Image (tube, grey):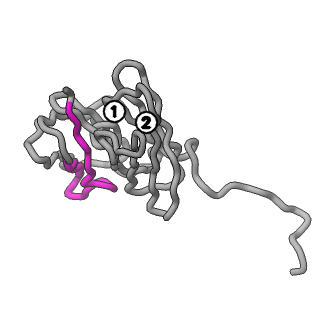
Amino acid sequence: GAMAPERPLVGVNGLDVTSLRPFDLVIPFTIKKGEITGEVRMPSGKVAQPTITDNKDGTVTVRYAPSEAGLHEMDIRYDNMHIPGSPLQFYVDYVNCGHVTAYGPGLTHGVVNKPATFTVNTKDAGEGGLSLAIEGPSKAEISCTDNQDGTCSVSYLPVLPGDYSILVKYNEQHVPGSPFTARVTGDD
């Protein structure tokens, strides 16, 4: 054909914060004088910058607007030196879909002797053996609770700073992105 027909239309085929689950996390750290910046890296070959905000309570909150699914990671640095708890690492997923899945701050970042928490969604997942574990540089203790909304909540206590692998599984099948890696920091 020589040209388009007499019925043209423009539309967006990519995903955004309206259609994907966002990234939002909190880290024990304080801004005083200087500057903090970062980078988030995508499986699809893309790159983007995060936002950092100091809460004035002895913590910084870190945020990013999503556009791709899969296993992701984020670098954060103050005056070009990495902060304690950087890099962060986690999975991004379609929260409205029917597959068994897991997300929250505790599987991305932890703090020694503090209860770190996250959620597993089982809302349309069927039936079987639901399982949960952590493998770290020392043995963390773990608890979990079934909710009337059709989700499971999770809590765990690490004891020394380092990398801790989180495992989530249902009916002998791992959730997408499992095993994940949390990075644990010092409380003092």
Dots 1 and 2: beta carbons under 8 Å?
yes
Q: Distance between the residues labelled 1 and 2?
A: 8 Å
The quadrant the N terminus occupies is bottom right
Residue 120 shown left or right of residue 32 in the figure: left
Residue 42 shown left or right of residue 123 in the figure: right
Q: Where is residue 82 in the image (x, y as percent from the top left)?
A: 34, 45
- Residues 4 and 52: in front is 52
Q: What residue type is labelled 2?
A: Val
- How would you classify the magenta stretch by its main secondary structure? strand
Q: Which residue lies furthest to the bottom in this view?
A: 1
Q: What element carries label 1?
A: strand
Estimate how packed mark 1 is, as few (under 14), some (14 to 19) or many (20 or more) residues with alpha carbons within 10 Å.
many
- Residues 32 and 66: in front is 32
Q: Is residue 174 above or below residue 156?
A: below
Q: Which residue is drawn at 31% across and 48% down?
A: 126
Residue 141 shown left or right of residue 153 in the figure: left
Q: Residue at x 41, y 19 (%)?
A: 56
Q: Which residue is drawn at 46% across and 58% down?
A: 42
Q: Position of residue 115 (x, y in %)?
A: 21, 29
Asked which quadrant contains residue 60, the reply is top left
Indicate whether residue 169 is drawn in magenta. Answer: yes
Q: Is mark 2 on a helix, strand or loop?
A: strand
- Residues 157 and 7: in front is 157
Report the magenta residues as a range.
Answer: 164-186
Q: Which of the labelled discs sits on residue 62, or is there none?
A: 2
**Which residue in the protein does label 1 denote?**
27
